[PDB]
Amino acid sequence: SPQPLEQIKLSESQLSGRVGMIEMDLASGRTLTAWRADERFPMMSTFKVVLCGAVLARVDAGDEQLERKIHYRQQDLVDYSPVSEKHLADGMTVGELCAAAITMSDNSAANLLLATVGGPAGLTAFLRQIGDNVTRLDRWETELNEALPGDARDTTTPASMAATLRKLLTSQRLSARSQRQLLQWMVDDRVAGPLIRSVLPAGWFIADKTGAGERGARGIVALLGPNNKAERIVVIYLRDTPASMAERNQQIAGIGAALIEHWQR
Ligand SMILES: OC[C@H]1O[C@H](O[C@H]2[C@H](O)[C@@H](O)[C@H](OCCCCCCC3CCCCC3)O[C@@H]2CO)[C@H](O)[C@@H](O)[C@@H]1O
Ligand SMILES: *[B]([O])([O])[C][N]C(=O)[C]([C]C1=[C][C]=C([O])[C]=[C]1)[N]C(=O)N1[C][C]N([C][C])C(=O)C1=O
């Protein structure tokens, strides 16, 4: 494979789309590779990690419990809700809702949790509280995936998302137990985690949350590293490409391959 930046450029050319990417040391926050890192991209379902960061902050403060059971109704549901559809009779705990939102990308689970943090406006306020002055959530699932060309709604930048993820996972803004919980939810991703492991060389750690939207929008936020360690945050977003889902997946994988072959920097 090419060097990381060369592969990122190739991916843009082949996709006829914009790619945004950051590679950041998790421990120190050092930025290693950056491409369009200050440009806006739809978050899509990658927002679900930040959402559950906000939930955990409420838990730490004693304003929420992961055990608390929410008994929601069918009228609360939106599409792509494989876990929450199973529990109209019996409900789900707040912790189960975060697990479903992150590991299964469950949209109704996400919307239920979003309401508990004050909706899109409340999550945006939480982001400002942790010093992210760029990321914004404006809509609910599933409209937040619309990815209209030039629309700033529901966007982040690779740089802001990476910094925000590092803050949530490591800065001690969250309790130790909450930091550990957020990480484990990403480790447990069922949408892409197992597939990614199936193509990673032996020894490479992965934890992740993916997202998909309209007009080619697709993304991943991840922890990756050799020696079975979460060494780096890697954030990749695609937008405004007519390419197939299969190619979008392959292009993101190709950027990963370039990172893997050229890790020491
Ligand atoms: O010499 C380096 C490695 O080269 C190949 O590994 C290949 C692997 O066979 C392939 O499946 C993967 O595809 C890339 C898969 C990437 C997975 C998704 C990446 C995510 C992770 C973080 C967020 C962005 C994307 O590339 C590597 C590097 O060429 C060999 O198979 C392996 O034995 C060897 O250790
Ligand atoms: B997450 O925010 O990435 C979850 N993403 C979704 O639920 C997407 C999945 C999807 C992507 C692309 C296409 O063409 C369909 C579904 N949902 C989504 O983008 N759309 C947008 C809004 N639309 C309303 C008519 C949906 O129902 C929908 O699910």
Image: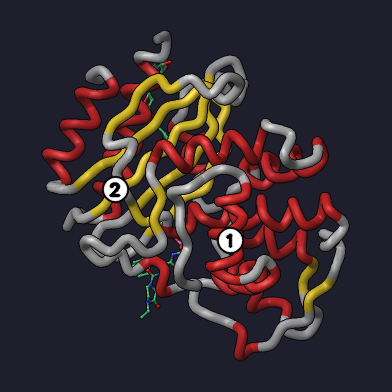
Where ligand 1 lies, by quadrant?
top left
Location of residue 95 in the rendering, given as x and y in whole percent from the top left corner: 77, 59
Location of residue 113 in the rendering, given as x and y in whole percent from the top left corner: 66, 68
Residue 109 visible within the image: no
Which residue is labeled 2 in the image? Answer: 238
What amino acid does circle 2 point to? Leu
In the picture, residue 226 is in which quadrant?
Answer: top right
Mark with earlier residue (1, 2): 1
What is the spatial separation of the Cα atoms under label 1 and label 2, in whole angstroms? 23 Å
Packing grade of label 1 (10 A; few <14, some 14-19, many >=20) is many
**Could you say which is closer to the camera, residue 151 or residue 75?**
151
What amino acid does circle 1 point to? Leu
What kind of element bears circle 1?
helix
Residue sitting farthest toward the top: 264
The residue located at (42%, 27%) in the rendering is: 23
Which residue is labeled 1 in the image? Answer: 123
Quadrant of image for the C terminus: top left
What kind of element bears circle 2?
strand
Quadrant of image for the N terminus: top left
The residue located at (56%, 39%) in the rendering is: 165
Using residue 41 as the reference point, say whether residue 129 is left or right of it. Answer: right
Asked if disc 1 is less than 8 Å from ligand 2, the answer is no
In the picture, residue 157 is in which quadrant?
Answer: top left
Location of residue 264 in the rendering, given as x and y in whole percent from the top left corner: 42, 9
Asked if disc 2 is less than 8 Å from ligand 1, the answer is no
For residue 207, above or below residue 204: below
Residue 112 visible within the image: yes
For residue 207, above or below residue 28: below
Using residue 41 as the reference point, say whether residue 101 is left or right of it. Answer: right
For residue 125, above or below residue 142: above
For residue 64, above or below residue 187: below
